[PDB]
Amino acid sequence: DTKIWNGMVGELVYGKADIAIAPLTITLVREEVIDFSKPFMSLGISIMIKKPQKS
Amino acid sequence: DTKIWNGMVGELVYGKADIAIAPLTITLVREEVIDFSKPFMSLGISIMIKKPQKS
């Protein structure tokens, strides 16, 4: 409704922070409001399961 | 010696091509001469072996 970026983006768009070195997902809506560097950590959705156990 | 980029970079730096949509490794020496987009295909050096031959 207010279309206010909160968080670290709201600290970068509104000038409260000079840069954000943090785990931050580069999305297209975040791309248009702040300039990202090239990604240092490629990742994605992964599968966490228990380790198998003898039974 | 001549410090001439060949290839598609030599087609982009020297204006012979307007854009390069191609499999192209984003390196730092290539970053300074042409502007890359954010990477669409994260990858790296992988291990190709034969499939096991259980018979």
Image (cartoon, coloured by chain):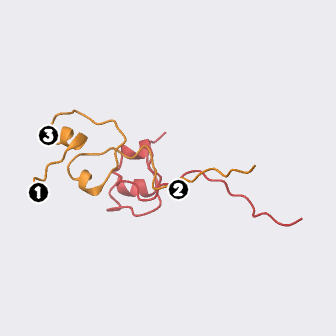
Chain colours: A red, B orange
Closer mark to the observer between disc 3 and disc 1: 1
Where residue B18 appears, as percent x and y from the top left, is: 22, 33
Instruction: Give the structural element (helix, strand or loop) at label 3.
Output: loop
Which amino acid type is shown beneath numbered disc 2? Answer: Ile
Which disc, if any, is residue B1?
Answer: 1
Give the Cα distance between marks 2 and 3.
36 Å
Q: Can you say which quadrant of the picture contains the N terminus of chain B? A: bottom left
Which amino acid type is shown beneath numbered disc 3? Answer: Tyr
Instruction: Give the structural element (helix, strand or loop) at label 2.
Output: loop
Task: Count how many numbered circles sit on residues in the image.
Answer: 3
Q: Disc 2: which chain?
A: B
Residue placed furthest toward the bottom:
A54
Q: Disc 1: which chain?
A: B
Q: Which residue is mark 2?
A: B47
Q: Which residue is mark 3?
A: B14
Which amino acid type is shown beneath numbered disc 1? Answer: Asp
Few, some or many residues within 10 Å of mark 3 (<14, 14–19, 20+):
few
Q: Decide which of tag 3 and tag 1 comes sooner along the chain.
A: 1
Where residue B47 appears, as percent x and y from the top left, is: 53, 56
